[PDB]
Amino acid sequence: MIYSKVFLKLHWGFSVVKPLAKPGFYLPPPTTLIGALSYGKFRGVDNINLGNVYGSPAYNFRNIMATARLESEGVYTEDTGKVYIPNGRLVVVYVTDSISKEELEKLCWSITRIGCKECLASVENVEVGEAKKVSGRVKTRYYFRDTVKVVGRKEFLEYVTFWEENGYIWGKEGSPVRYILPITTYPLASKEVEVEAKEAYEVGGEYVVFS
RNA sequence: AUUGAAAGUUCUGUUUCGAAGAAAACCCGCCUCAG
């Protein structure tokens, strides 16, 4: 199980609107993170024949684990929800085993935007390594699933709804999955939460929780 | 190539006209550079 870390510098922020008034999300979903990685290999093409229907040139990277977190302060504003965090820093962790270290590192440098066109984001540095699996009590900053238990004080937790990769195809809505975000609503920031969990990969001290 | 893809809330307008800080008032009364 290989892992990679990337540091991104945002220009003005990101904007992803909720499916189904156009409120937006607080942090990008894993689908956007996987699509940004896939942009490095599928550049120039917008429709691929999956075999039955044209849905996206991203239905092949669906099994790559990804998380992300903030490192600065921002504000969420509706004026079409937007998350303004100019000159901020984003840390993205990719955990997978499908490809070797070289391919993941090459695709990691090829991230251009997160969300829509205006949300450009440069790349400052990357790290690649081998991760270890643990199950003891850990402290994490990355968001995780709803079913994961919590031992600490419930004070900085929010509930959001994301979608699986089934939504990659047009004319079809993805499955609803609940997610827990350790975020302060105003001003925007990230806080540490202690969880027990069952699977946690150590990617340099900042344990990443998946289930 | 990411609930992503496709879009200007843009066009037209004077804070303008008018109204003396003006009138009265002494620096002035005393002193050899001398043998």
Image (cartoon, rainbow, N blue to C red):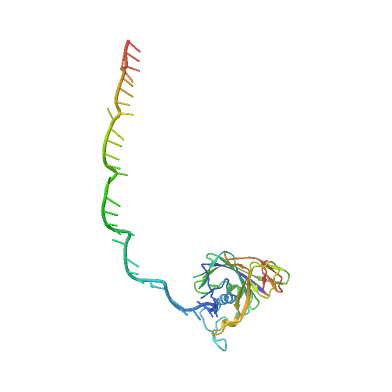
Looking at the picture, tell me which residue is in the foreground, A47 or A136. Answer: A136
- From the viewer's perspective, is residue A61 above or below residue A193? below
As drawn, the residue found furthest toward the right would be: A136
The answer to whether any part of residue A200 appears in the image is: yes
As drawn, the residue found furthest toward the bottom would be: A52
Residue A87, image x, y percentages: 53, 64
Residue A207, image x, y percentages: 67, 69
Task: Tell me where residue A138 sits by quadrant.
Answer: bottom right
Looking at the picture, tell me which residue is in the foreground, A129 or A59. Answer: A59
Q: How many marks?
A: 0
Looking at the picture, tell me which residue is in the foreground, A79 or A67. Answer: A79
Q: Quadrant of the C terminus of chain A?
A: bottom right
Task: Tell me where residue A51 sits by quadrant.
Answer: bottom right
Residue A95, image x, y percentages: 64, 74
Q: Quadrant of the N terminus of chain A?
A: bottom right
From the viewer's perspective, tell me whether residue A76 is left or right of residue A129: left
Residue A126, image x, y percentages: 60, 68
The answer to whether any part of residue A59 appears in the image is: no
Looking at the picture, tell me which residue is in the foreground, A11 or B7. Answer: B7
